[PDB]
Length: 473
Image (cartoon, rainbow, N blue to C red; front, side, top):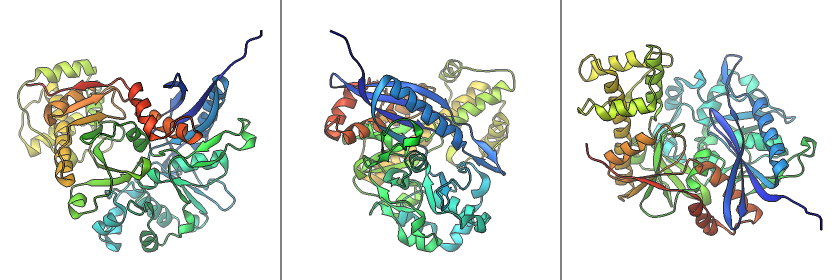
């Protein structure tokens, strides 16, 4: 008797603002197994003045991951998640008009002054639920059109990043709700495009693809790619929303990120679109099964990094272990800076900027290095603690635990700090969060798992949860 072979699976593509990964996951003895099979950089380029996404490189890496996936697994589907807000414009013959612009592009700096002239910001808030930010898709489209109206007439379709890569693979247009709710074009109540806002900003609805929900089977990968007719599935296409899939669905649970997309929030059954929620800086995005991911952006673990790269330029390079020791040791109570209100510019030196801010707004001393690190760490921790206190007031509920999702292998100590200042259990072990949520969505769609029912029992089996509790000092 001659022996034969291979294993059924689902391919998750997780594109981030700085790096991308391809992760395979499959059922193996009714347990979820997940193998990372490709990882890469996502280096932006400057194109005709604008910061832009290298789309030809990204698509190349997606195809290289699928060929690698087909090599070791039977792939039943692929499913792509990305960062929010950015989009590509497709002309009338189905070609990319230009390279998608990076959310950090200076085109939107100053843009809210023009929006304020055409609508009160709270009204826009009450129709879309998003905290009003310059990077939001609406204002990006507003600038892009304003900067070159004649150019802009050539757009036939506007594709958010996941829809762009989905279009490139399949030829077909769809925008899934989770990415649509980062745009300031989408109504979290009806969970579809907001025609009132479209009317106001004079954008024809035809420009936007049809709204779909997660699990939608869009189409198969085009025959000319040579990869086979693999179904492409619309997953929770915004990376944040895929990560929230894997958070337990228990009453008193919050989630937190300190990387990339730093935030704190909770899943709600329906949006909060009050002046309170508006004035308090909260956003209503949409996630799996139409839930509201109700959340407040914070500024994340990045000012630490920048103060590190600023200590390298002074020939004193610290490791996080150095930083932990340095901060853990400095036991005084130092000033607390309102990190949210800081305006530290793009290519400044962080040591000097922070020294300066402190001198202007608190007091003066030759701040030793551990002390600037302590102040920075305590201030970001306090930003999160205040964020939760508003979250509790607005939601009429007190919560008990906080799952760490997203970026922050570097953040482990920041997590224990979060526990110290908030009084809540902090759980970690969810660094695969996004890929898990991406994968299960596809497994349900191809019928490997029954529903969220089983999916929860399968994720919880998979996760190795570790708790942090408030320590004195």
